Length: 505
Figure 1 (spheres, rainbow, N blue to C red):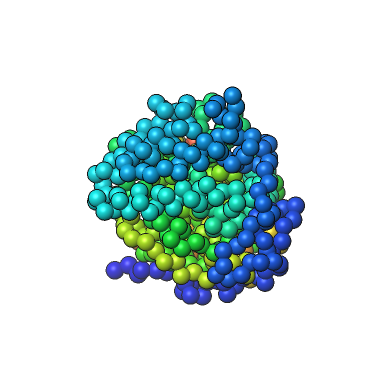
Figure 2 (tube, rainbow, N blue to C red; figure 1 turned 90 degrees about the horizontal axis):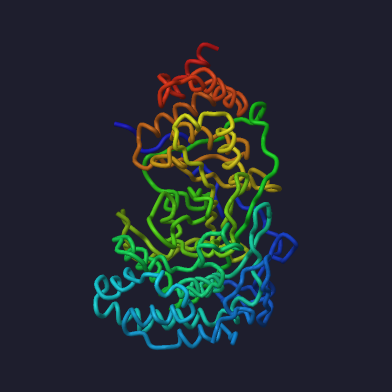
């Protein structure tokens, strides 16, 4: 029988907080927006906002806040924020009450936004007492934090545009207020099909969670209301950092002399459960979070539900270009799940916090390409694209490699997305090697794949092939077995080809 895991013992892999650099003082800079009072930051205390009082920017470089005095609506032109306040400061006893409240400041979508799934959740899925608690406690508490937005998020939030290398660090409390607003669909300029300014950003308002008959919707709502119940009953005290990273220069893959690093590979366990303290790869959509606020539940998006603070990145994160990723440090897990997705129960996150009061949970969104024609991914241009995407996700400029955790990852962009698991494993191993990080690879039930990955890594390591030598083998595979292949896949597979090439010298 196959073993459960192979390679380096997982406990010998580096992880946070132990491996981490000494953090300098948290402070704003040209590359770092910090929305809280750093001098008053104290463990277990809700951070205070900086500035003390709301300051507004309504322009193309910052989030358009719903509480802006430039957020106008027909009443003459009147305050949409005052209308939002009046709409939401009402008693809800039936789901149509919530629908009508939300539509008061979204009149243009009165017909276009269906609320069938919300109605069904409220009346059919919840028991009478659960529904009562929803509308007597949770929803009014959600309204309170949402309408406190100008007192909570006092500092303009910059848009993380393409090509920006920039960080935003905000409190979990600030994020809660932002997400309560997203639930009540209050963010202006984020709704229209013909959107101009925000066409290159993901949806943020939660309207599409309320629509349709999908049996998935009630499980999404359960998971989000678990979060909203938690943060309203006990205000979170941590910080979260969102960093856009955009690299212009990449390794010279054909000549790279860096050695392969360590590997732990296993067909049991999960990235979030067993990669604690490690850099956790989110198998992302280029629109980060993908369809999380609307339809379907695909590769990675479950993470955005169980760590819902990740969702707020959609407010300010432009669609990722090929050379870009988003790194999120400090999100908390609020829910556990089974499966077929179903909310199981709440989660009490036990992670330690770093010196900036950020939970030791680092997630990187990197989007694989889709391969609608299988052989496309072996073309050198496409191998390099994926290498560079992974490398951007793994690299930490100016951080010594000894202070970097192992990368916790798995079958990135494979299955129905068209990626070949064995190629993608080797691509991630090479990118990790170039960024000088070890790899913890979860195959999620596939024990033969675990063995095949371990066997290849062992062979390449023992024969002392560096990144460049392995890349050259991938080029040979393309040129000799793929370029002229007239069938969907070649007769000789990649790993067998690599073994024979090296063994024949």
